[PDB]
Amino acid sequence: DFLPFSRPAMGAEELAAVKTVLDSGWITTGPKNQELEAAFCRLTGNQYAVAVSSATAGMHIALMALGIGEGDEVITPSMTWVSTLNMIVLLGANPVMVDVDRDTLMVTPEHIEAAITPQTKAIIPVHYAGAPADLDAIYALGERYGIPVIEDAAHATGTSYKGRHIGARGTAIFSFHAIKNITCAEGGIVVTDNPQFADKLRSLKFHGLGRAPQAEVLAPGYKYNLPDLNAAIALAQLQKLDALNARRAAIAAQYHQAMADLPFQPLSLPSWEHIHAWHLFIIRVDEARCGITRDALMASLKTKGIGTGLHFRAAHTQKYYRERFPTLTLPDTEWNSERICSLPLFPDMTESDFDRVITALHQIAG
Ligand SMILES: O=C(O)CCC(=O)C(=O)O
């Protein structure tokens, strides 16, 4: 009875939503997309939303829409999924990786400010694991220097920062991937407060068109539209958001309590006021403190039928980036990269499950 680190919360509502779309005969981008965009604006408090085929696609067209390319620099942490780095590189721009807080894994204003040059054209903070980054300080940097801020909110559907939802202002990109807080297997959405930018996003995700028979390419774009079939599933999940996040939050609490009697070190919560979406429950496994390495712990758990994730192996430690940036050193990122792992955490997780994990942890924890 394998216990994976994540499971989608799929039930009768998701199936019913698909049945309705299949029965209507309008299966690709249409009214369900328009509805999902309207719901994300209502959810966040922002003015415009562009649904896409994934958050990676959303990042690609966001950077593309800013006109980022050869000669430009984009500040981002290395502690994030490589898709952001890849999109910066593939547009022909230069990623400038900066370090993160040692216990929250979030990019600091200091690390960002120190990397700013006249070539910096975007700053991409990540709301890590469900908690929010220090937006007030980051936007201030953005405004002082005239640099766009594009928030990676793939872990943050349901996250709040100092009384306001992530995505309420500025530009934020959410993900509907299978292990994310809400899902339609693959999908994402770009929420923004800028109408000209939103218009560019809509065109770039659909062939650069301004479909009608005499529609025409205004400027070449990609194909990243989200089918209504998947959009309807996302809408069904979005309706369940509070209950689903409430279950993750409760399980995070037990983990917290359980960790008191264990040597593994969970992340620290940011100091600012916030609401945590609890996308992941990450722990650090330092061999000298725990007696076991991170890799050994993950493999031990797997033997016990317990799955774990690794979010993330820092971008700068992966082949292409190691060879392109050989002298790049980011201590707090590397320290965590060698020691983090994500424990089972999903809305349908039971106590049999939970307790199964903790019992495996004690078995291995000394
Ligand atoms: O299954 C996918 O399409 C992507 C999975 C992913 O990005 C991940 O490693 O977390």
Image (tube, rainbow, N blue to C red):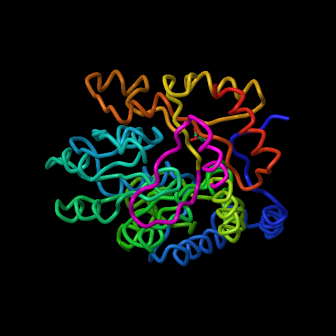
| Extent of the magenta region | 253-279
Residue 271 magenta-drawn?
A: yes
Q: Residue at x 25, y 46 (%)?
A: 111
Instruction: Give the position of the N terminus as an image quadrant.
Output: top right
- Is residue 77 highlighted in magenta? no
Q: Quadrant of the C terminus?
A: top right
- Observer-nearest residue: 185 or 248? 248
Name which residue lies at 48% across and 57% down: 131
Question: Which one is in front, 187 or 332?
Answer: 332
Q: Position of residue 362 (x, y in %)?
A: 69, 32
Residue 284 location (% of width, % of height): 51, 35
User: As drawn, which residue projects farthest toward the front?
Assistant: 261
Which image quarter has ligand 1? Answer: top right
User: Looking at the picture, how far across and down is residue 227, in whole percent?
Assistant: 65, 59
Q: Is residue 312 visible?
A: yes
Instruction: Determine the image quadrant of residue 164.
Output: bottom left
